Image (cartoon, rainbow, N blue to C red; front, side):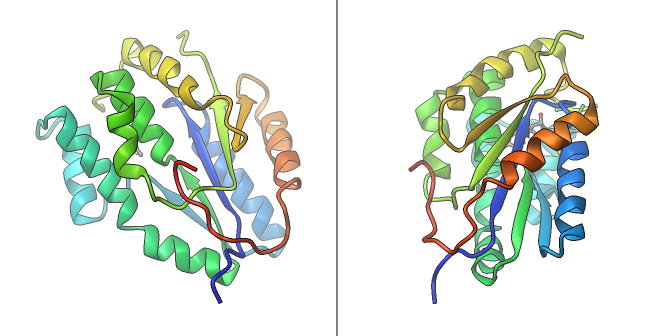
Length: 200
Ligand SMILES: Cc1cn([C@H]2C[C@H](O)[C@@H](CNC(=S)Nc3ccc(Cl)c(C(F)(F)F)c3)O2)c(=O)[nH]c1=O
């Protein structure tokens, strides 16, 4: 009746870490293996909430640090019913960015308290695995600056030792990064299981 049957994979990483390259490669690989999979992205800029987030990111409005933080969290909550329904049926979800982005970006770029940042996402569906595309920032949107990216790299380390968190050296060839990811995916437990939730 109520078991999670599909698998839920999140990609995390700084901007231009290769997330969408790798997530598209993973989705293609799963589809070639007959697995039904939905590719989702956060923020979803299409929703009423996402359209405001979009203005914020393009600097078409300005918003206070707590206001935008909470909108990013509400934007995930408005997808929970749909993600749950997919996973309950056995459809997999590959998702570019999630609650980890919310915490790392707001604490890193906006200097918000980590616990305060985590609280609104408590209760979101927990993914089976997070692939963190690790690219030290050594080299249009509000967080674009290399100075801003360096602060976020540090804050992402908050999650580095959780057993769901898989560090991926994203400085390697694209094919080799993808092979690395496919390998970890084959380790995911096959059978249905109870849903788990952040930040358990
Ligand atoms: C899910 C989520 C995302 N973000 C930020 C992360 C990222 O800095 C920003 C960028 N998002 C998207 S969809 N695209 C994007 C495209 C180009 C460029 Cl240059 C950038 C950025 F400015 F970040 F570099 C971002 O959205 C957040 O700040 N909090 C969140 O919870």
